[PDB]
Length: 49
Length: 49
Image (tube, rainbow over the protein chains, first blue to last red):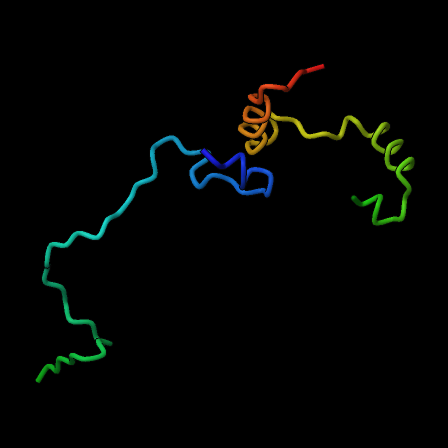
C-alpha cells in the first residue's frame, strides 16, 4: 500500500518479490519442552561424575 | 553520470545519450526489470507516446 510512495524510488525491493510459494514463517510456541542444558548456560552447570 | 564525472556540459551529455539510445536495458534480460516495468506501466498517466 505504500511501497510506491516510499521505497520504490529509493531502490528497495519487496522481501519476496520473486517467489512462488509464500514465505514460510516460524512462531514462538509457548508450549514448555524439555531440552538439553546448554554447556555455556550462565547459571546452570551439569557435571558428569 | 560518468560523462558528468568527466566535466561535460548539458549539451555534451544529451548528444552522448542520443548516440547511445540502444544501451537501455532489456526487460527480458533482467528479472528485476520484469516487475519494475509492470509496476511502472500501471500508472494512470503513462502513455507509450
